[PDB]
Amino acid sequence: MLVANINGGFESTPAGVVTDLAEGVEGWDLNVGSSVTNPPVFEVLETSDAPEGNKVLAVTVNGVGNNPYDIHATALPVNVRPGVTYTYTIWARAEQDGAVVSFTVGNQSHDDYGRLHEQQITTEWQPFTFEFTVSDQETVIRAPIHFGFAANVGNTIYIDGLAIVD
Ligand SMILES: [Ca+2]
Ligand SMILES: [Ca+2]
Picture 1 (tube, helix red, strand yellow):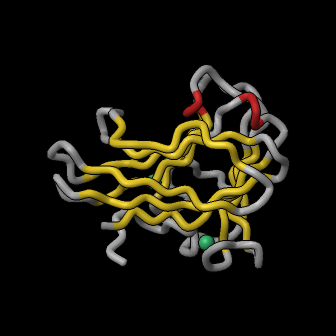
Picture 2: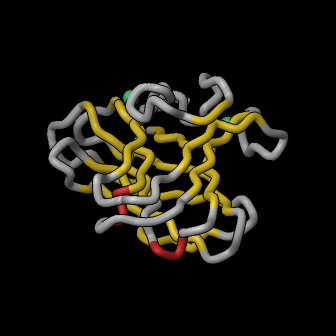
């Protein structure tokens, strides 16, 4: 496929705990909000339990901040053409039931093109998919995934297989 995002399945990244949140995982920016006082752990896992390849990203939430994006994994850059309609697809599961995640796509002004908001994540892998249109003149966009929900404290969420395709 003609994919707009880079390293969507983490297959380019060495397994281990991420200590470089900005540049340790090619094609993604991980960050933690200054309001989060019990920080999360991000880890690339090498596993047979992957929907794609053998790597997944595991996000362990230990506490939250003020905003759901205060614990996030954002695909960036996401290279796109104005006016085009894309299909976003990703897989996610959690260690315990009751996890909540938002899968968004938006521009550098932090306006969304679309999202799957506050999705219930279960202990089995499930696909989350939506279409969105680049409705402005942007060519470099981003795909923020929000993990900072109280529901997630004590849980680990696993993501894999992000594809943003024409
Ligand atoms: Ca993968
Ligand atoms: Ca980066």
